[PDB]
Image (cartoon, rainbow over all chains, first blue to last red; front, side, top):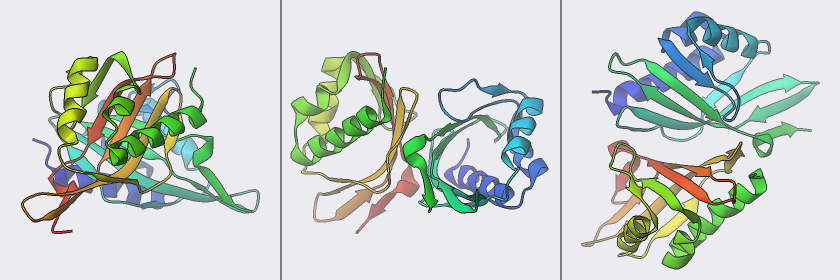
Length: 125
Length: 125
C-alpha cells in the first residue's frame, strides 16, 4: 500500500520535474486515466493527453519551484505546501498553493487538485 | 457564495476556537449535515452530534494550534497548513497536518479533512 516514502518521493519528483521543465517527467507520474483540477473550482482535465497539454501550457515561463514544508501523506493520499516562482512583466511573481494527490494501487497519481487563489499570488514589486 | 476572505475568516475562527477550547464555536462553523474525516483514510463522522463528540474528545488536553502559512482559498474551498502541539504522560508532541475545508452556499463548512500521517507527528518537540 502506498507508503509515505513513495508518495513523498513522487512529490519531490513532481517538484524537480517542474523545475527542470521536464514534461515527460511530469506526465509519467500520472495514471493514464488521471485527473488534474488546477485551480480548484475549474473544469478538471481527464487523460494523458489533456494533462500533458495542461503542463506544457504551464511551462511557458521558466518556473522555480520548491516544497515549503514537510509532505503530508496517509491512506493513499498526499498534500504539500509549495511555491511556484517566475518573472511576469519584469516582476518576480510567486504563487503559493497547496496540492493534493490521490495515488492508485499501481502507485501513480490518479487525481491532482491545486488549491490556490488571488490571495496566494505575490510579487516583488 | 463564498469569498476567500470569508473562508479564511472561518479558518482562523476554527484555530482560535481550538486554542480557546471553544467547542460551541467550533461546531457552529459546520453545517448540520457536515462531515469530518480526521485523519484522512478514517471513518468520516457525519452530523452535528458526531462532530461535537469528535472535538469534545480532541479538547481533553489543552491544545496549542497555529497556522504556519497563508490560507489557500478559492471556489468554495480552503486548505491550511498548521500545527497541533500538546502534552501527555510527560512528553511534548507536535502534529503538523494540512486541513481541507469545503463550504456550502450559506458559508458553512460541509466537509473537513485532515491529512497527516506518522511522518507528520514529531515527539519530544
